[PDB]
Image (spheres, rainbow, N blue to C red):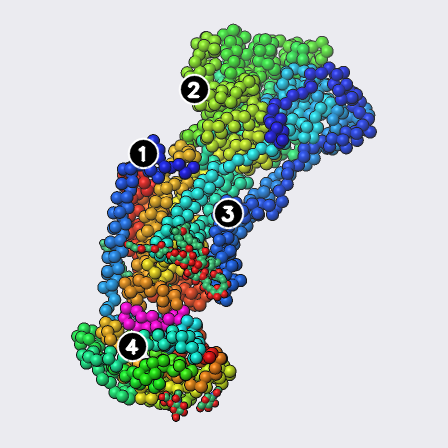
Amino acid sequence: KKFIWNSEKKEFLGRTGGSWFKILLFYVIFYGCLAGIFIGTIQVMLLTISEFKPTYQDRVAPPGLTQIPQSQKTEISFRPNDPQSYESYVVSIVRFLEKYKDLAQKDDMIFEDCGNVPSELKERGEYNNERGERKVCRFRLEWLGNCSGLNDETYGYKDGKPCVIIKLNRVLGFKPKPPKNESLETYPVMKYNPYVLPVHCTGKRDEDKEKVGTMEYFGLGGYPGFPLQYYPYYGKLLQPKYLQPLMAVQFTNLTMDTEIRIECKAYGENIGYSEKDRFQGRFDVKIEVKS
Amino acid sequence: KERDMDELKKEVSMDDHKLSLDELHRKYGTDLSRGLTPARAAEILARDGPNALTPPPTTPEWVKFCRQLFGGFSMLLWIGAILCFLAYGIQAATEEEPQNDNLYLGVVLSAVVIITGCFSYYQEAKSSKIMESFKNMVPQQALVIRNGEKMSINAEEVVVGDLVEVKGGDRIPADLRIISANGCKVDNSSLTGESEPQTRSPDFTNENPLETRNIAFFSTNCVEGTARGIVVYTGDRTVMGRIATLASGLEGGQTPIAAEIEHFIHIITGVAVFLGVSFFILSLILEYTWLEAVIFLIGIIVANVPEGLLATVTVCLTLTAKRMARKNCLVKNLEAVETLGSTSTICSDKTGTLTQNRMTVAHMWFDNQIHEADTTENQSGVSFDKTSATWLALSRIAGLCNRAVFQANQENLPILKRAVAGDASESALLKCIELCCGSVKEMRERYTKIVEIPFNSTNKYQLSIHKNPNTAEPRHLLVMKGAPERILDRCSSILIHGKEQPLDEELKDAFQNAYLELGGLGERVLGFCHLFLPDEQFPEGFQFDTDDVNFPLDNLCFVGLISMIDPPRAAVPDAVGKCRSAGIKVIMVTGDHPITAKAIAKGVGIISEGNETVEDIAARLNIPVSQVNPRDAKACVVHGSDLKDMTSEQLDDILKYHTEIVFARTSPQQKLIIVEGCQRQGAIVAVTGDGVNDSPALKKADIGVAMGIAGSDVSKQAADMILLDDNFASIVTGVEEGRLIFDNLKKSIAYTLTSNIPEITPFLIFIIANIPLPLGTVTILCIDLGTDMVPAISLAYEQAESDIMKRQPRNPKTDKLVNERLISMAYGQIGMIQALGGFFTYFVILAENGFLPIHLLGLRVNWDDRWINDVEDSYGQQWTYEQRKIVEFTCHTAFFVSIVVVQWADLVICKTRRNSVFQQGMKNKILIFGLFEETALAAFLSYCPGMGVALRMYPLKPTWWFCAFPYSLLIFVYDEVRKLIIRRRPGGWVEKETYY
Amino acid sequence: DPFYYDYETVRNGGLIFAALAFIVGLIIILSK
Ligand SMILES: *[C@@H]1O[C@H](CO)[C@@H](O[C@@H]2O[C@H](CO)[C@@H](O)[C@H](O)[C@H]2NC(C)=O)[C@H](O)[C@H]1NC(C)=O
Ligand SMILES: CC(C)CCC[C@@H](C)[C@H]1CC[C@H]2[C@@H]3CC=C4C[C@@H](O)CC[C@]4(C)[C@H]3CC[C@]12C
Ligand SMILES: CC(C)CCC[C@@H](C)[C@H]1CC[C@H]2[C@@H]3CC=C4C[C@@H](O)CC[C@]4(C)[C@H]3CC[C@]12C
Ligand SMILES: *[C@@H]1O[C@H](CO)[C@@H](O)[C@H](O)[C@H]1NC(C)=O
Ligand SMILES: [Mg+2]
Ligand SMILES: [Mg+2]
């Protein structure tokens, strides 16, 4: 039943020789024309959008609160006694913070010195090539309290006091707006700088909150949040080496051999949340220092 | 050993009819005049079984449900489900939270199979239900003589060997051996097929137990006369009982449409497994693991199984079947609606199927002129000439010199289809006078009868003397009728143009040739004459004689002749002509005498004018038939006597070298043999019959056509198509609908198979280039089980692109339903453009949100990660899991909409195979409704509140609906120029490679 | 802000289109 091998009419696999050439040539021309038409339509579409401004951004609003080190299942578990069980977090933290090294922000044509205290949004202008490349607000690695990779390369994991550097999702043309102190009656006690997007970490249930211990916030000017002098973002085309604001949270005095789930939330008018997106404006990290 | 029982039943029957009255009563042990004692009845009744055929085997209701639930198409769906469903069972007992991508799919495929089974069961059940409301048969008891006393008992209470008396009007209970008859004429129509009622004589006449006159058969009605007989066979042991049991034990076979469906599944699996294995090699070449390679192979084979094609095909066949049901062309087999379209040889029955099985007045001879009376069933033929006085004389002789009339309830019934008591000839005459000369009720009493002389064996005559009607005053009218050669001798005066003339040989021989003309035409002639007794020489009051005949037997006035035969049905000739126009070979298979079969064949179209048989040429050359060459004869009459002594090779020789064949005097078993011979050639055969002798032929054939009323219940149950209106034109309608639905099936299948390319390609490249999923599974279900349902169904309402009844029947081994050209067009060209349009929309959406098409390469790795909430786009922005996932779902929805957009043009191009869309016109209202409903349904699936939460199909930005427009327009233009080139360049490479 | 899309207007327009297309199709199939 599978002897379509050959025939007296010079058939191979089912058809003759010249027939194979005719059909193969037709398919080559046909598929080539189809590919050319598709690439041409894709070119016109590429011409539709711009180089420094996406046509749609409502799918990225509000931004999300990401945490470093990034962890699978958002669990940061290790044995403080063993320097090997926490090497993954150290590697990821070092890899991410290497872009913020003191030596990385050398040139002035790209890196601009910005205030040591949070200031107003530094608007560099418009989104065009008229003003060429843009300035980047430098972020000193020392602004992170005890997890800087400057004095303790481990960042605290050596003596059971980890650090989870928090970061804000980059959004082109986004201007964070901290909540006015007039409406300050819902979020917990935090430092109030009208130029700082606040971030506060807490537990999740009546047990996690109790077993957490003591939170230690580290940031620019000692404010638990992000300074407004670093926004808005101008895309990767106008600001190639832009450094976003960072913040660190150290969980000193954590219950050993116990997994505690903590949630850090960034408050603000421009910051929303979602019951389906566990990372929109907030994030969850369950840590366990099982020595 | 049932293979031998079937052959034993196939063998012609034998009997013990040729036995002396003493020998017969000796073999069965029964009194010739008193029958048997009542105690002797219980000795046989509880011995072999009541006189009744064993009911057919019963197949419980749920059996058909399971039959449709399994099938062959449903089996492919069952295996596809099985793979997908068995995967989730192993997944549930191990992980914490799986995905429904395969579980929901498996349950959906299973539900599809079950739903199709439910719908099919409902339709077939309705067919059987209406068939049951039409087969309401009531018991008929027999008049048995036991202990010397007459008693009417149920037929089932009759046993073997007990005197049975059958009166004129009673149906023969069981097979009887006539011992004493009085002019009994049984109607062996349903059993042997003999149209003209055959008389039963107690004396043995022919060796054949059927042609002989001393045997009464089961299911035969005694037209007239009375007779006595001893029961020979009972229950299933009877002739028709054995024939019925043989029919119940025959194999139905494989319908042509089922074989086409199987071939289609074969090609489907061919591409499925081919793509699966080739992509398995490709996946491994891309350095993927064997675990993933097996996963891919299974996914490719499964994704290549058309789920929605089952319901579409079922409803597609149901629509045409309903159109058949509207014209009384009921189909018990759902797939039997197409069998007619593939038929290339129709074997028809003569008596009952082609003819009306009703002796009717055909021609009349008066004033030396033949007058053909209309022989139609609905009275829609050319009216004869009735203005001369001779017509009045003939009508008087016929209406007056006739024993009986209609019955009690025969008042509202039509003149033709109403019952009449008496001989068939008398009924034909009565109907002719009732339709051409007013009425016979008041015409018979107006001429009071005095002395009537019925038919006699010696000096055969049938006359009667009546009184004068009005004031003409001749005072008497003696009417007589009989054989033309006998009535001609006892006549001297001849009525012509109104007056009288002598018996000159000049016109006497004209009458002779007229008799031979009507005889050779295939009719039964009867001469009619009357005479006015001169009241001056014979009294006006009371003067008659009966023992020493006084009325002048000779010197009568001959009026004319009246021929008669069972005429063919109204639409039979035109239907045969139409079937021959489409290339269908019409072959007659009857058990009637050849003298009548040849004439009916020449009159209906089975034998055209000019074509001579092996006998016609010999008669035209005055030479023995053994001299002429059979190749010179286009048509031929095959006698059943010679067919018995034939081999398998000779039958093939008869069918090949002869176009117009007429099989006469063929037993039911020989009909089955002829059917098998026709099937040996490899051509589709369709048998049309009515009597029980057609049951084996209607069962073995690819499709049997039975008469709703003129057909017996046995052959009606053994057939596959019922004609409730008996309109033989339904055969022409059925073949037209079969070919039409075949073409529409090709179109709908192409439409469904074209959507699989842009369905599988997103997942294929999702694995190949490692890009975010362009199209999800839920959307695929919304396409094959949603939008495309109506367009695929509406493609069945399409109509002929040319004269379908002009082309030859399709070749089973050459013209396939789904060939490689269809795959080349759907999977090769149209589907490819649809896939390109979908990818265009995908890149458009992603690039507009910041993820340029270039940046999407290799992004799936971290795109599917649920914890990498800082995915950078081409603009440097960081996206969380749910944000990019929302973009993926709002991208999948647009891909589905793109599928609908390209499906518009795909439906338009698949709507026609050769003609242009403008030559055919989009007059298919269901198709336009399909486009509107499809578009509206898609828009609803995207903008309904809660879809991004229920089906994860987010609303689309309006500017997306025009992304696939240029692609659909391109598809339409390309296929249009393709069909235009095929139209202006037939037989070219374009047609030989793309015409599906 | 450019970070807001009037999904309500487009959604309502889509529902309106679906209703109109469906009733029009019904008119064509239930033609008189
Ligand atoms: C950061 O690290 C230093 C260590 O260099 C911490 O020093 C603590 O000093 C206080 C005050 O005497 C002691 O109570 C603690 O025991 C010291 N801790 C350790 C680990 O040595 C210091 O508290 C840390 N945090 C801050 C906010 O400065
Ligand atoms: C040979 C000629 C006729 C082909 C010309 C191609 C035209 C018809 C094609 C090429 C580029 C296409 C456009 C490219 C970009 C966009 C923007 C998008 O948001 C919707 C589709 C839309 C609006 C396309 C519509 C059709 C379009 C204008
Ligand atoms: C035979 C073929 C060409 C008919 C093509 C139908 C075209 C004209 C119709 C069918 C589907 C329609 C779209 C369906 C849904 C929407 C969303 C709505 O909120 C605005 C209109 C919009 C964007 C429609 C525009 C017009 C449209 C594309
Ligand atoms: C952890 O340490 C702080 C130090 O100020 C102490 O007040 C607190 O009670 C401790 N909490 C737990 C839960 O051990
Ligand atoms: Mg018949
Ligand atoms: Mg059959």
Between the residue at mark 4 and the residue at mark 3, the CA separation in whole angstroms equals: 61 Å
Between the residue at mark 4 and the residue at mark 1, the CA separation in whole angstroms equals: 68 Å
Could you tell me residue B149's position as x and y percent?
A: 81, 26
Between the residue at mark 1 and the residue at mark 2, the CA separation in whole angstroms equals: 41 Å
Mark 4 belongs to which amino acid? Glu
Q: Chain of mark 1?
A: A
Q: Which residues are magenta?
A: B866-883
Dot in front, 3 or 2: 3
Between B705 and B75, the one lying in front of the other is: B75
Could you tell me residue B743's position as x and y percent?
A: 40, 41
Mark number, residue A98: 4
Mark 1 belongs to which amino acid? Lys
Dot in front, 4 or 1: 4
Q: Are marks 1 and 2 on the same chain?
A: no
Between A163 and B819, the one lying in front of the other is: A163
Q: Residue at x 44, y 68 (%)?
A: B949
Q: Which residue is mark 2?
A: B634
Q: Which residue is mark 3?
A: B75
Q: Which residue is mark 1?
A: A10
Nearest to N terminus: mark 4 or mark 1 = 1
Dot in front, 1 or 2: 1
Dot in front, 4 or 3: 4
